[PDB]
Amino acid sequence: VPVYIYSPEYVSMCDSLAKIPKRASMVHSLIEAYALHKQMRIVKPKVASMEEMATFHTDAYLQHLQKVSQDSIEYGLTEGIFDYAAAIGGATITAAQCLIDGMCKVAINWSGGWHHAKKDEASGFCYLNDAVLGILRLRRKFERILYVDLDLHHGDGVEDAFSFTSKVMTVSLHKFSPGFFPGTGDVSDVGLGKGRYYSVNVPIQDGIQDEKYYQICESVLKEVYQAFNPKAVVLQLGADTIAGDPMCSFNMTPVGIGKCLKYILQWQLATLILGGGAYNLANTARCWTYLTGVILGKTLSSEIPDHEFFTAYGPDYVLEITPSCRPDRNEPHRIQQILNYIKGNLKHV
Ligand SMILES: CN(C)c1ccc(C(=O)NCCCCCCC(=O)NO)cc1
Ligand SMILES: [K+]
Ligand SMILES: [K+]
Ligand SMILES: [Zn+2]
């Protein structure tokens, strides 16, 4: 039975210092309104210790972050932000611990996925890279970890953490366009040194929809699985790809993301599920509730059930999201060229 990382205090903490308010409450409240929590093993998250956070971040960065939370320019830098970051990092580590111990094959921290943070630098509103911390916890048991990042943005912090190693392969599908954050992650970015070809990047343009996205994702993950043979997976599912997000870049629905998730779940590997960037509150809850249903194999009712935040689901009050009427800017020949480039990189793996 999947593990669901959750406590009322954790959700309150996540919404107190969140970049987007009440997002954690709405996601959990919708999952609860669909009664999906009854089909999962609810595990209270522990708070990450200083030593656990220092598995990736430097002592100087963690000490400075802890002080200002009580030369910030140097570390890419709010009251209480350190306890917030330690709570989210501890939640992802707790999920990874559940996977190590064989408590489950899928463990979910929807409030995690803060993929931009570097060892000594906050970045992209990420003060602590819980995805890296979770991978490093999984490295206690699993020899090869696959990190898949389906956020709108390039998972640069996670890729940079493992750029020099072949024990962790990072795969990011993201918007890539001059001026678009964080600006890295071209298909030519393949890692460095012993990690060369163990970073995979799929640059994508505005307006992609469910069918073409899944064709790209399935093609990449199929070749990655055969070449890399991962023993565990960490999957980042930032909902800022979803139609109606203020980012207004991709044109996805949770159904397309869900097919990517299903393809990974079929591998039967230990799988750590994370959230990520997401800026439409109601659509974020829609997406991650639906994806929770996919994890559980359950079909959900279309009408948003009556619950605390029902009035936020206008004007339609249904779970389904409709794509926006705007163009797909992705040229099929550019996409194929990217797929050819990646296939050639993975022959080296
Ligand atoms: C209030 N408002 C509309 C905004 C405030 C800040 C930014 C921004 O700094 N953007 C640059 C940093 C982008 C970080 C993206 C985080 C993300 O989703 N990563 O996956 C933009 C808009
Ligand atoms: K991504
Ligand atoms: K790597
Ligand atoms: Zn994002």
Image (cartoon, helix red, strand yellow):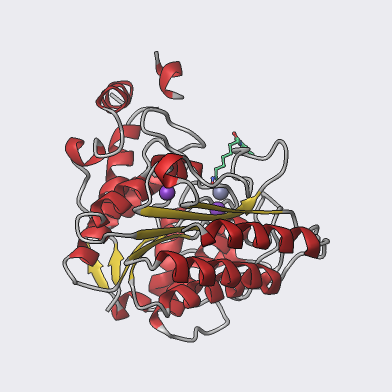
Q: Residue at x 36, y 38 (%)?
A: 128
Q: Which residue is found at the position 45% from the left and 62% from the top?
A: 27
* Residue 155 locus on image (x, y percent): 51, 47
Dividing the picture into quadrants, the one containing residue 272 is bottom left
Q: Position of residue 343 (x, y in %)?
A: 59, 63
Q: Nearer the viewer, residue 40 or 8?
A: 40
Q: How many marks?
A: 0
Can you name the residue that lies furthest to the front here? Answer: 348
Residue 114 in sight: no
Q: Position of residue 264 (x, y in %)?
A: 45, 73
The residue under the point 67% across, 71% down is 210
Residue 129 visible in rendering: yes
Residue at 31%, 33% in the rendered image: 57
> Percent from the top left, x then y, of residue 65?
32, 26
**Quadrant housing residue 253:** bottom right
Q: Is residue 239 above or below residue 89?
A: below
Viewer-proximal residue, 85 or 304? 85
| Image quadrant where one finds the N terminus | bottom left
Q: Is residue 234 above or below residue 267?
A: above
Drawn side of residue 276 relative to residue 187, left or right? left
